[PDB]
Image (cartoon, coloured by chain):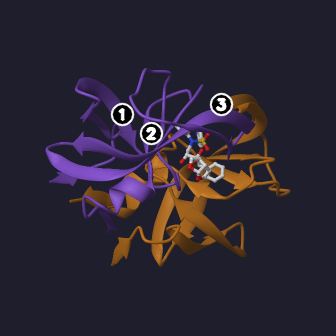
Chain colours: A purple, B orange
């Protein structure tokens, strides 16, 4: 679909069999989700945002479904203000910016 | 044009008679630019993201040219790691997400 930006580009995602709301975020390299239980092993990592750096749990090769489109990649879990879908997954679903 | 998301969506912008590089950021409500000494009045503001909040100066009705597309609106100025063009101006240049 084509998504205009008059309001936040919020979409429903499916991860770990649960539905959630997330923000399509072209300014994010990586995908960062709010605290949640995800299966599989994870490694401690750090990620930096506008306000500094936070501790996150890095899950690799996670299946996420974004508006029906499937992606399999890295998901960082930690104290983010919002579920953000970053470019690592936006590329998988074939997302581009157009003006 | 069409901007893919393999790499950061960096574009050249023109603000206050200066050329800068900035992210086209669908995850930013409002445009935030690295510290610069714009003339005119401003209002204090705090904006938050990953890592917490930063203090910024809110200027209104600032003209910005993004890849030849002119826009005018709110520009926040502060110690951001990156110039980001937010939805408040992305809508003005006709920018959409497409997948
Ligand atoms: C977290 C979002 C809901 C909001 N952010 C925009 C977002 O695109 C930032 C924009 C951004 C980009 C680079 C550096 C700082 C902030 N990206 C970001 O935090 O990404 C992190 C996860 O992937 C990594 O890649 C970049 C940093 C990491 S934000 O920078 O904090 C922000 C908040 C409010 C406004 N008006 C403008 C910007």
Q: Chain of mark 2?
A: A
Q: Quadrant of the C terminus of chain A?
A: bottom left
Which of the two residues, A19 or A97, is positioned nearer the viewer here?
A: A19
Circle nearer the viewer, 1 or 3: 1
Pointers 1 and 2 in contact (C-beta within 8 Å):
yes
* Residue B33 in picture, x, y percent from top left: 70, 54
B19 and A30: which one is in front? Answer: A30
Image vertical order of residue A82 relative to residue B7, above or below: above
Q: Chain of mark 1?
A: A
Residue lying at 24% horizontally and 43% vertically, measured from the top left: A66
* Residue B97, image quadrant: bottom left
Q: Are marks 1 and 2 on the same chain?
A: yes
Tag 3 residue: B48
Comparing B68 with B21, the one in front is B21
Query: Residue at point 42% right, 34% down?
Result: A40
Residue under pointer 2: A84
Whether residue A31 sits left or right of residue A80 in the image: it is left
Q: Which quadrant holds residue B16?
A: bottom right
Please give the residue where the numbered disc 1 appears in the rendered image.
A22
């Amino acid at each position: 679909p084509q998504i205009t930006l008059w309001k936040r580009p919020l979409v429903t995602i499916k991860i770990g069999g649960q539905l959630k709301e997330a923000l399509l975020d072209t300014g994010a390299d990586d995908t960062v989700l709010e605290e949640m239980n995800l299966p599989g092993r994870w490694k401690p990592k750090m990620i930096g945002g506008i306000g500094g750096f936070i501790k996150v749990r890095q899950y690799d090769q996670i299946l996420i479904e974004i508006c029906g489109h499937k992606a399999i990649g890295t998901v960082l879990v930690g104290p983010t203000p919002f579920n953000v879908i970053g470019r690592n997954l936006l590329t998988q679903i074939g997302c581009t910016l157009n003006f």
